[PDB]
Amino acid sequence: AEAGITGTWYNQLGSTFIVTAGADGALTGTYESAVGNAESRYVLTGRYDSAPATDGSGTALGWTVAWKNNYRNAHSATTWSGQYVGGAEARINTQWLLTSGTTEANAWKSTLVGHDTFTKV
Amino acid sequence: AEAGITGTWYNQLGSTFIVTAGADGALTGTYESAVGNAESRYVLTGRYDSAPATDGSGTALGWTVAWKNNYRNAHSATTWSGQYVGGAEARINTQWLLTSGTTEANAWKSTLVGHDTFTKVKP
Amino acid sequence: AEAGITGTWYNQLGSTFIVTAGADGALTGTYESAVGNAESRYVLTGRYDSAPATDGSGTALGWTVAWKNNYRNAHSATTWSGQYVGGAEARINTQWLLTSGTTEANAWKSTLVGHDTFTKVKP
Amino acid sequence: AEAGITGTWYNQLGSTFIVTAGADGALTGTYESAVGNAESRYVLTGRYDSAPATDGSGTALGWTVAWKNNYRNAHSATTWSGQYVGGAEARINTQWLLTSGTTEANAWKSTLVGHDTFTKV
Ligand SMILES: [Cl-]
Ligand SMILES: [Cl-]
Ligand SMILES: [Cl-]
Ligand SMILES: [Cl-]
Ligand SMILES: [Cl-]
Ligand SMILES: [Cl-]
Ligand code: NA
Ligand code: NA
């Protein structure tokens, strides 16, 4: 729990997540996607339970990335919600929502949902 | 635009969102929830598109709140993904995911999904 | 109750849902969508709790529509999960998932999520 | 595509799905869950694209199960939306929504979301 979130993680698509977990609940770092209208690293910010468990539970966390950087602006943002489980093979299991900015006419089809599993391998 | 988003907003459950949109695309503030094992204000952090399209398209954004403060700890975190629509009646329409920490065993039932609409209060 | 659900309903996008709830918990009917690459009516099938609680709790149900009929094929399917609330103004509040067939390559972007509220029409 | 959906599939939790895909788009069968306030088989009904692809795409499908049978009534329903991909190792990749019947007071927390991958192994 805690500390252990800090590091570089990769998900099944090959995207890389580099985070620092702060003693009080903050999550800061950068994200580089392997898919999308993404190009380079994007800033990410989130929050986690700094006091999880003590039944063998995971540590709830979440973070956001607005897909805009010095190279591209996809006019979308993705949020990942999930939990961290440490151990010999630590992982972060997440479900994400990706919203694109649309006109009201296309608001019904603005959000994609998926799931990503990140490991340090 | 940072401004448009900066302000106090409320949603249909009676919760309060106080946010400041920074020039760099950052979102920081506090959230007061009307439901759940929540008590007092919680810190929120998010990101938004500081350069949206010039299209009556909404401005994409998202933020997270881990439900732990100095008074309560619910061992859960919520992320909201949506867009801000400005105008006379500005709104932030979102869909959210609430994940609870659980044992591997109950992980299948760790996440709730819903939707919230926030209305800005200002004269 | 089967009845309560049986009828014609419309949602905020202007789509039409005609359903019959059978005694065994079955749902069958047709759906007319106001959006997407849809044209005409599509067949729908679902299930609902034919023995709900006796609690002003809603009646859980869900249904699917694959968007293929004799006129169009969008190579996608939508499932709606929600509950029916009866009363003077009966409503079915749902959250839906729309999955498109894609290549493994674009599977990450195969599913959309949203929410729909249906209002029953009847005098 | 088509036909190939018919059979017995299992997901990572150990739940079993037995379906018959009908020439015109219907999906019928039974489901036995490994988790929840479930007990025995429950009836399931759905729809699939009977005419998918011709770029190597999967076959979109979805189905519902109301968790009520002769033994238990959990007052909930689950819908799975996803696509079938056949081949040497066929699978059905899905995301699901589980709604429980609640009073309006708890409507905000009525729906769970997850993902399941089913194989014939
Ligand atoms: Cl990614
Ligand atoms: Cl992306
Ligand atoms: Cl809230
Ligand atoms: Cl519709
Ligand atoms: Cl299952
Ligand atoms: Cl279940
Ligand atoms: Na809330
Ligand atoms: Na629709």
Image (spheres, coloured by chain):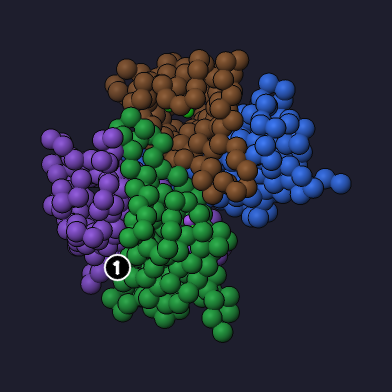
Chain colours: A purple, B green, C blue, D brown
- Secondary-structure class at tag 1: strand
* Residue at the (45%, 64%) spot, across then down: B32
Can you give x and y, in whole percent of width and height, for residue A117 in the image? 26, 42
Can you give x and y, in whole percent of width and height, for residue A94 in the image? 32, 45
Asked where in the image residue D14 lies, by quadrant, the reply is top left
* Residue at the (82%, 45%) spot, across then down: C122
Q: Mark 1 lies on which chain?
A: A
Is residue C84 found left or right of D115 in the rendered image?
Answer: right
- Whether residue A70 appears in this view of the structure is yes
Outermost residue to the bottom: B123
* Residue at the (67%, 37%) spot, across then down: C55
- Whether residue B85 appears in this view of the structure is no
* Residue at the (36%, 30%) spot, across then down: D117
Asked where in the image residue A119 lies, by quadrant, the reply is top left
Name which residue type carries label 1: Lys
| Most foreground residue, B29 or B69 | B69
Q: Name the residue under label 1.
A: A68
Q: Is residue D92 above or below residue C99?
A: above
Is residue B44 found left or right of D24 in the rendered image?
Answer: left
Outermost residue to the front: B71
- Looking at the rendered image, the quarter that the N terminus of chain C falls into is top right
Q: Residues within 10 Å of mark 1 (few under 14, many from 20)?
A: many
Q: Is residue D39 above or below residue C15?
A: above
Does mark 1 have its CB less than 8 Å from ligand 2?
Answer: no
| Most foreground residue, D99 or B57 | D99
Can you give x and y, in whole percent of width and height, for residue D53 in the image? 42, 35
Q: How many marks?
A: 1
